[PDB]
Length: 61
Length: 109
Image (tube, rainbow over all chains, first blue to last red):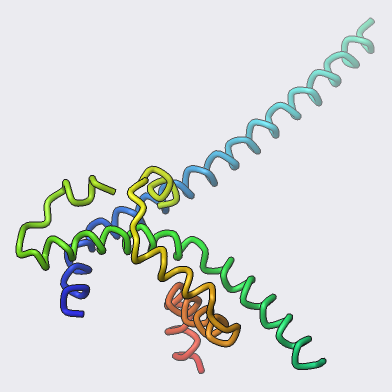
């Protein structure tokens, strides 16, 4: 049991890396999802503005 | 019959708890396998180099292909335990995964 306990103190650094990697991975996945939403929002607003312009030109004609 | 019916629900809870501790479980197993080899070198009296680990979270489990003996048989013993023993293991796993929420629950209690 002394052996096991001694080993854990050495492999602590690996532990930190494993954890931090997992954190960064989840950060990226969430960030991706948010950017997708913002793209969709902007696409939708372009279709709104397109229709409004067509009807503005219709009134002009 | 009620005893056996209750046992079925115990297994359902155990399943949920196992899913609640899944990520922690994987991280642990990577480090347990690494520790197995690490201790061998220490017990020999030699140095623990990077090559020790090279012989071998989720990704690293798949990449590693050095299937170890003892650890696998240990897992079988665990799977082949009684439902009671396994339910209690599930509880310990949950506490040791989310320790922060415990410290907090108790401070407020």
